[PDB]
Image (cartoon, coloured by chain):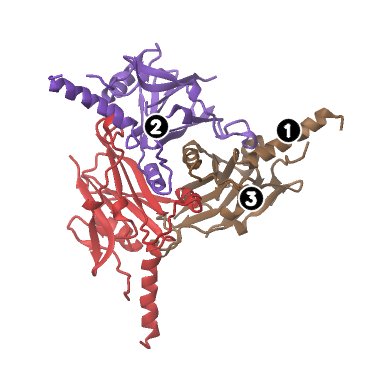
Chain colours: A red, B purple, C brown
Amino acid sequence: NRDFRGREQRLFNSEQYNYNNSLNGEVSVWVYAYYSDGSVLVINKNSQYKVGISETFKKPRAIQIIFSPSVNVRTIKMAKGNAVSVPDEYLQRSHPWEATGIKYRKIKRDGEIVGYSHYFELPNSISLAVSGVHKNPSSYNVGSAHNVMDVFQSCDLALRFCNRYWAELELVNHYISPNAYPYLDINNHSYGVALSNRQ
Amino acid sequence: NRDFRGREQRLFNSEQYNYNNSLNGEVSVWVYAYYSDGSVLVINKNSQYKVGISETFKKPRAIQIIFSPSVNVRTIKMAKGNAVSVPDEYLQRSHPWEATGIKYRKIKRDGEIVGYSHYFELPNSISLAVSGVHKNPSSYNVGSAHNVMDVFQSCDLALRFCNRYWAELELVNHYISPNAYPYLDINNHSYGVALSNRQ
Amino acid sequence: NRDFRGREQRLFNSEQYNYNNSLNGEVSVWVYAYYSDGSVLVINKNSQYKVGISETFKKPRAIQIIFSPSVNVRTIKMAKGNAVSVPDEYLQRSHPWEATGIKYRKIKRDGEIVGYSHYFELPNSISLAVSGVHKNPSSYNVGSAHNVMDVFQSCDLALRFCNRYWAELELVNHYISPNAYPYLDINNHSYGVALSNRQ
């Protein structure tokens, strides 16, 4: 226990894990749209407290939604609409979302959860929105009298990124891996970096 | 009262009406922009709790704002700005909105309210925003300690649609009618489907 | 004190100042992006209660953020991200914002604060978000049980403007000055109109 360099390295990584999972940290969502030409569109949003994406897609063959490990899985919500942005046939009969958390698989590296994935192939246009709330183990209510304005400001402060990659290989090499992001490729292989209590 | 098929049909329609008007249901807004070439741009937004649209328009001849019957008319707000998105001449003297609910006409079919319309012709660019809150007969406050985060998530989950139709006839046939939407055409004719207690 | 025209003129201006600073009034933010060809992109957002902008920029040489005098400087927050919209190297170690209010200079005309400026030159792409909350001297909490829905509606009602000007001279003449906006040019000269207790 006299290897201070070893101890600092472990603490360096754990701190990252734990900061992300605190209420001071990010919650992140990615939407991946897969096209028949093998290219992939990603939209990412990163924000405090809660985060979401809402976009319309020209026919993808498939969609993968990934959240960061800092999401509360139980609060995940998805509105998947038709070509005119109606969630369920007609507005009059539409619940504005489905709570799809049960369908999310854990993306794991070395036994650690690096994210959560929901993947679905499709049978024109879809409108798709997805939302999740940052984990909060604690009693402190972020939407209190005292903190609600900070949540309002987080809506302004959320950062969006959107790009198209020509191939999943390009996505893995130039997007997922440089940025320490979680991912699940078509061969069901998990990508990500485990940090908690690790060197 | 032994025509169960008749009873189920009536209940099927009433349930739709009532679901829409519950707090589990959609509130919807449409902005229609009318151009001198007779084409029409629609923006629609559909969300839980509250909904709005905010866009800038190259000179339309006219604007029609329609809300679903699930809006609370008294909470309707509109910010109509100039070419640089200032609501009232100068920011220093601008109230950020006007409460225009009194100007909304009921769109009715068979005596039932299928929506609310505000229509105005214009005398360059306008910036236009409009907002409304879902009806709530009940005592339950959606923006409480316990439910405010769900309202935050509804901002992420809101679905937008935007298209241009070449003629009002095309709008009526391919947009309004296929989707059971309320509408008021230039001849003041009402479109929509009455559901409450109806077969 | 029998010059009623003089008294009304002074009151006319003071009322504008004071209305802006009330909770009924606007809070405004501008982002200015400066390019090597000498052109300038402005984004402006105007809303009640709180306001923000979030955009990605192809390499500007510099950024100036200006807020209206109705902002509370202490609540200003900025997220400046990399090319993939991450605020601080990696999501796991990112605080979603910095509170940069201390760096803001007062833009003054005739001793009156007409706005606040933060200016920074840059060493590809940046993602940039900025947010601020309208001043509230009073005890009344805008995000209360009773008023939180109005804050939700202000998110719908916020108006955005975006344009490119070819030169700072064009910005000053055609954008800042016609609209009584505050500004600080490259020569450190202040623009704006003083209103409080002034003729």
Residue B14 position, x and y percent, is: 26, 25
* Badge count: 3
Farthest bottom residue in view:
A2
Per the model, the C-alpha gap separating discs 3 and 2 is 44 Å
Q: Is residue C100 above or below residue C150?
A: below
The image shows residue C169 at horizontal and vertical percentages of 65, 42
Q: Is residue B33 above or below residue A124?
A: above
Hey, what amino acid is under mark 1?
Answer: Phe
Q: Nearer the viewer, mark 3 or mark 2?
A: 2
Per the image, label 1 sits on a secondary structure element best described as helix
Report the chain holding disc 3.
C
Say which of C185 and A30 sits in front.
A30
Crowding at mark 2 (Cα within 10 Å: few <14, some 14-19, many 20+): few
The percent coordinates of residue A113 (x first, y second) are: 27, 64
On screen, residue C113 above or below B119: below
Give the amino acid at mark 3. Answer: Tyr
Which residue position holds label 1?
Answer: C12
Quarter of image, res C171: top right
Whether tag 3 and tag 2 are in contact, CB under 8 A, the answer is: no
Specify whether residue B92 is in view.
Answer: yes
Label 3: how many Cα within 10 Å (few below 14, some 14–19, many 20+): many
Who is closer to the viewer here, C17 or B125? C17
**Inter-mark Cα distance, 1 to 2:** 42 Å
Q: Which residue is mark 2?
A: B137
Looking at the figure, which quarter contains the N terminus of chain A? bottom left
Q: Position of residue C192 (x, y in %)?
A: 69, 42
Dots 1, 2 in contact, CB < 8 A:
no
Indicate which disc residue C116 carries: 3
| Along the line of sight, the residue nearer the viewer: B99 or B144 | B144
- The mark that comes first in sequence, 1 or 3, is 1
